[PDB]
View 1 (cartoon, rainbow, N blue to C red):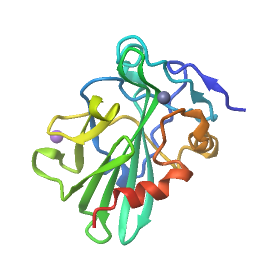
View 2 (cartoon, rainbow, N blue to C red; view 1 turned 180 degrees about the horizontal axis):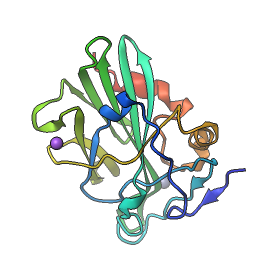
View 3 (cartoon, helix red, strand yellow; view 1 turned 90 degrees about the vertical axis):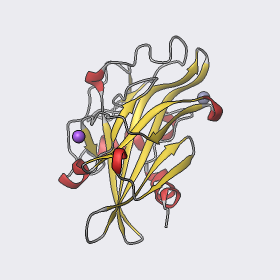
Length: 212
Ligand code: NA
Ligand SMILES: [Zn+2]
């Protein structure tokens, strides 16, 4: 059965995003803190995360571990692509912060044109809403997001950016398999972090990210 595993030993999920999910994956620029890590493996092991002491990016800056998740939904007339990233800790300063970090972004597409009608990005419990993003905030089909510490909200958060970002290996909800979905769905694996694609949170990510 799946067990906890060291954050730097858990194997990533292979790429399983659909062509549409891959097309619209936001770029993610790490302004500060951790790079993204695998929260789970194909066998349903889950990351033990990191204690939020030491430097905010210590032990979580290995780019070979990068992962993104996506769960698709069709929602009130739009295709909604709910992306998520896991960082092993969410630390503002040594001892201030949390083990685990789950971030999310919802890309809403027009039913017909598959044009981006809007993107929303997680800001610890709230969704920032970007109707009709463009210009310096999009590169072709990839909206550009920055991850950074936001001490006023006691957490890291996502915002739209003009800086180029990474596109880590993209595992879809549907492609990752049952054991990995179970391991993300188990909310008690994640302390104070909340995976916005888990079964218990997908509905509120959708209604929360809605901007029409
Ligand atoms: Na580009
Ligand atoms: Zn905490």
